[PDB]
Image (tube, coloured by chain):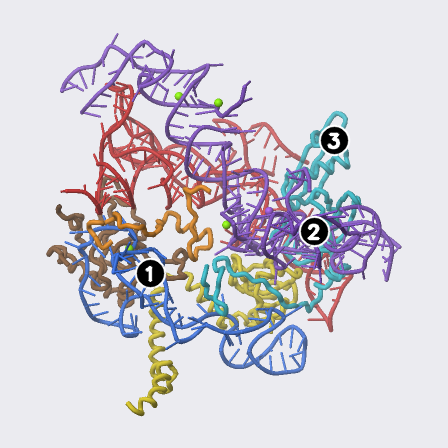
Chain colours: A brown, B cyan, C orange, D yellow, E red, F purple, G blue
Amino acid sequence: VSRKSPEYTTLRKSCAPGAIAIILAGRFRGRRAVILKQLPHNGPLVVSGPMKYNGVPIRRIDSRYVIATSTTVDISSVDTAPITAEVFQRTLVSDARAQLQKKIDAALIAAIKKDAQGKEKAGYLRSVFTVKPGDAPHRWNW
Amino acid sequence: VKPHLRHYQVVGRESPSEKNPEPTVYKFEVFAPNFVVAKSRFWRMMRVKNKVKATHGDVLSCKVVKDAKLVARNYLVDIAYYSQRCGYTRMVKEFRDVSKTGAVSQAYHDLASRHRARYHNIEVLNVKSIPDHEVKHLSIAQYHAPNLSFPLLQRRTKATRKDRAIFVKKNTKRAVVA
Amino acid sequence: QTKQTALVRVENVNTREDATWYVGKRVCYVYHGKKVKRCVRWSKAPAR
Amino acid sequence: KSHYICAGRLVRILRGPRQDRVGVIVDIVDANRVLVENPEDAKMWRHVQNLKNVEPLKYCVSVSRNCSAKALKDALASSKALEKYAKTRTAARVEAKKACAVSTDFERYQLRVARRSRAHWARKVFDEKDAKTPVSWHKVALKKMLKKAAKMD
RNA sequence: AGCCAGAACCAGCCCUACUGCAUUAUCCUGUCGGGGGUCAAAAUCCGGCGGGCAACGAAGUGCAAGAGGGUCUUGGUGAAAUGAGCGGAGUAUUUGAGCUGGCACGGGCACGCACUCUUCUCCGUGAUGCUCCAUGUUGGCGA
RNA sequence: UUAGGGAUAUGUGGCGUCAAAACUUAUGGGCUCAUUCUCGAUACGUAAAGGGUGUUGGUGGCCACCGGCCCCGAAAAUGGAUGACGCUUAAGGCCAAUUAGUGAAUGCCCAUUAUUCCUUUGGUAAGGGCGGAAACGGAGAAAGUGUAGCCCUUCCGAUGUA
RNA sequence: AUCGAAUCGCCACCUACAAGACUGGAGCUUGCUCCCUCGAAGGCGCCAAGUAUAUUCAUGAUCACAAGACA
Ligand SMILES: [Mg+2]
Ligand SMILES: [Mg+2]
Ligand SMILES: [Mg+2]
Ligand SMILES: [Mg+2]
Ligand code: NA
């Protein structure tokens, strides 16, 4: 409750863990990922592809550069990802992060498969979002 | 859409005095855009017919009379209007509408178009719904025919405001610009 | 004219209710100069 | 041919808050205005409509002018014009438009894959039939060149 | 911490959210008679008397009280944060709405004057600081 | 009706293009066709009698009279002016709306004006501090018309020839 | 050869033609009825050459001209 406490957040309810989000900026613009959690002290979200489907690794992202759709996946993974995982000292991946990626991605894929509509959800995660001529994004539901 | 004039009943009197301890109470029916204009018309009528000024008068009541249920009827409207050249002229005209306020609004627009007469130069003497067998004008009588039917020709149909376009493909519906 | 405010017309946005959706969004004008000058990530990403 | 404006005629609303709803004409005021009502719809109580805002359909329930609600409800039910209107392709197009307006990113993806599947199978079938009867430009050219290649080369 | 970006939070300001009471009668509804018209009967219309709330968006009648978005339109990151908003303590307090027992109001009281539903309450930080300036987070650029 | 600048909202005037605004609004009603200056269309500001079955309505008895738009009546000196182009299911003329018989106060655009915020300057200006508390984040602290203004806080005015 | 640059849908199914007092075809009751193409969509394209447990993506580290490119 206390604003100084790290548990304090103000994230909008749409960006809840297990929601499928569209990336709007950065190297992975247009891909679809799954929101895992929000870092403490009202920090960024962390998302993963999983990397098998669309090639998006575990990554931090501001909630203002994401569209959180209404499609959800039930997640019950170990979610042992603190702030220290993304802090570095003052094709190459460390042998700890490389292991964390697998440990999370296997559980996430098991969750998607266990979900109903699993095949459709997998294809949905593989597809790419773009703005076509004649499109009106301001009129849509998400 | 809805008529621009409302129907008001205004009841008033002159303020009592030692000369007139119990003044006469008067009732007035007017069609006006709001109750302030309605009261202005009431006090003008009192001034020109009863020699009573607003500065020595009381307004007992001022309300709006509700319309009846919407039904297609014939309305006879007895109206009068002034102009400098002709003078004061009195007309009786029949209209088709669904309410008294609608018929009177029709009459005001009609007078504005065919005689250039403005609101403050017009007095409405009466308005009432009449039966089908008292209609004199054939242009109104034609709508009683029980077999009335006609097609809609030469229509100017516009698209919904969200779908309007500037340039479209000639035989299709695709928009090129907007 | 007052040049501190610009007017922008966007494709398929033809209504005031439509245009309200974009209040707060970021906007960019892209062009080119005559020489190569400094940019974001001039050192990290020389491809830019 | 054209559908005349008459008492008992079915219409569809074009613009405004009642857009794409069906009513029945119960009275004609003048050349511009009619009274419309549909008892089996929530927002279609008896009201006034301008004749530029309506679309006359092909059905007419046979009733007299300024009829009662009781006499119009059963006349509709007996005519079964609503069950007939629900089977045309313009009615289905209206329902499809509403369904498309209310749709999520997942449903748009589903529609995209359905259309892609249809196109793939269509082009496969076309290739198979063009093998028998050559109708493509490349097959017409191939058959035109085969006779020439049979000589010499 | 120099320069240039992005996001968050606090104070202020500016927008959009969330709203009840009165009034309906020239009205609503059922019969009877008339009048109307049709191929027959219904309606528009008038007069008798029986009831009444047109009450899901019924009036477009009068008066209304009910946190989400900006701040490259401001200042800041707690160097005295005065807060219904930050803290301590409990669970009750008292605002209305229904329903209750002298004078007023009209020719009975629609409920003026005096003595069950519905909501959060009480307490706190002076300047031995007269004035000014010095305090976040994440990247880009600068070795 | 005017100090130097932001934001919000208005006045007169507007919303087919020139030219910001109905990307040519409405789920409002009438009326009007004009062929060599010519239908008409922002006041102040630069044509009359009399005629017309052209078309639309009104009064009284198919008639006589009174209206609305339009047409004759209407003839000068460089080529030229609703400001130009153009407009006729108007972009004209009279009336009336605000997203429309749905169910509740403000469609939109533009000022050296209004409200509000920042800074300057001047007042018939209005308050406060100025015996160095002590110790040891930084410095300063003047009894003062006027300064690089002794230092803070507050309110109101600001154009101008001779 | 200078040259780095702004632009971000493709098609040998649109890329033929007329009408809007009227328009798929019949009737005769000429404004209704009946038939069926049902009279309100150019085709594709948007990440497995196609709807199916196939498959490399990271360190380009949280926005920055898309560090890509003419399907
Ligand atoms: Mg413009
Ligand atoms: Mg001063
Ligand atoms: Mg001066
Ligand atoms: Mg680039
Ligand atoms: Na002009």
Frontmost residue, A28 versus E141: E141
At mark 3, the secondary structure is loop
Q: In the image, is E16 to the left or to the right of B24? A: left
Q: Are marks 3 and 2 in contact (CB under 8 Å)?
A: no
Q: Chain of mark 3?
A: B
Residue at the spot of label 2: B113
Q: Position of residue F16 (x, y in %)?
A: 54, 53
Residue drawn at point x = 67 percent, y = 36 percent: B60
Q: Secondary structure at mark 1?
A: loop
| Label disc, if present, on residue D120 of the rendered structure | none
Which residue does the numbered mark 3 point to in the structure image? B22
Q: Amino acid at mark 2?
A: Ser
Badge 2, how many Cα within 10 Å: few under 14, some, many 20+? few
Ligand 2 in which quarter: top left
Q: Are marks 3 and 2 on the same chain?
A: yes
Eye-nearest disc, 3 or 2: 2
User: Which of the 4 image quarters holds residue B95?
Assistant: bottom right
Q: Chain of mark 1?
A: A
Question: Do callouts 1 and 2 point to residues on the same chain?
Answer: no
Could you tell me how far apart the alpha carbons at marks 3 and 1 are, in whole angstroms? 84 Å
Q: CB of residue at label 2: within 8 Å of ligand 5?
A: no
Helix, strand or loop under label 2: helix
- Name the chain letter of the residue that bears numbered label 2: B
Q: Name the N-terminal-most of marks 3 and 2.
A: 3
Q: Which amino acid type is shown beneath numbered disc 3? A: Glu
For marks 1 and 2, give the CA distance: 56 Å
**Residue linked to disc 1:** A130
Q: Is mark 1 within 8 Å of ligand 4?
A: no
**Quarter of the rendering containing residue B18:** top right
Residue in the foreground of this view, choosing between E45 and B34: B34
How far from the left and from the top, in percent, is residue G26? 60, 83
- Most extreme residue toward the left is A95
